[PDB]
Length: 163
Image (cartoon, rainbow, N blue to C red; front, side, top):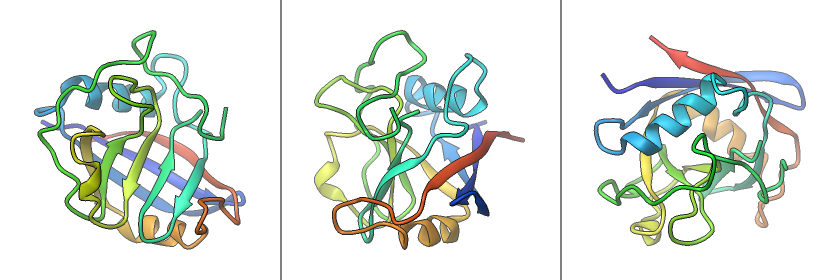
């Protein structure tokens, strides 16, 4: 019953592939619902057309700032929302987790881990995992850099809910 969402990724405007996620609504319903709604666009805003602005190989891909550089984004709740819980841990590649600016400042930015990142446990709310297309995340990762700047424009060309 956990929702599935997809991103169709493009690189300098050229199709790359689809990444799909399981969202752990059974665990973290408020956080899963935020990401689900932003992916469908059903509130009038969300992830379609946004970019992955920070990619560090071996670490994570970060996106969801739909100011396009890590300073913006907003939740579906009209303000930034609380850390729902830290039940789920950063256990390896594919983990989907909320970016934030300190305790209880969740908006729309998220990251996809490409490694185990246990130092983030208890700081960032894990709320999903890649289900299909981890290979597409691995292809995206190669356009990142040590300081996170991407060498090509990585975009969510389309997104929505599956099944």
